[PDB]
Image 1 (cartoon, rainbow, N blue to C red):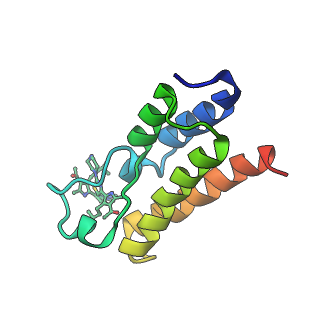
Image 2 (cartoon, helix red, strand yellow; image 1 turned 45 degrees about the vertical axis):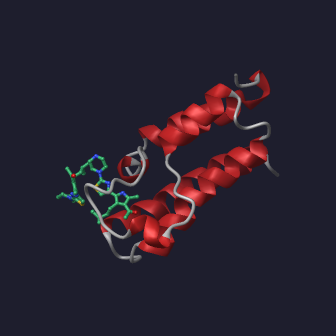
Length: 106
Ligand SMILES: CC(=O)c1c(C)[nH]c(-c2csc(N3CCNCC3)n2)c1CCC(C)C
Ligand SMILES: CC(=O)c1c(C)[nH]c(-c2csc(N3CCNCC3)n2)c1CCC(C)C
């Protein structure tokens, strides 16, 4: 399971999931709702996958956790136009994440 030293990451992820712009990213991108996603996006990521990975001990370090967070936002900007609803949400969430991360990494 998760080491207590990563509790700050668990909290950041909880706060991300609660954010008004998080709704696109809560669960894996759903083939029932959009086609051609995994054709393009070779490493899908979403907050529920991260939540389960963190809780089971699948992140040994905070850097591995942060890499998956950034993968959510990198995938979003690779697939979606910047002015689309999901594209805009990804930019909001990246800023929110990076602002929280910078409290710890400075
Ligand atoms: C392609 C993409 O990057 C997307 C991401 C990260 N999310 C979503 C999305 C949209 S609507 C929804 N849910 C989740 C589950 N609950 C119902 C609503 N997820 C997309 C598809 C965008 C567009 C093609 C509709
Ligand atoms: C239910 C669902 O599967 C959905 C699919 C495929 N797309 C969208 C979507 C994208 S953007 C937008 N709007 C609505 C009108 N006002 C705000 C912008 N709805 C949804 C609703 C999901 C909900 C979590 C927001």
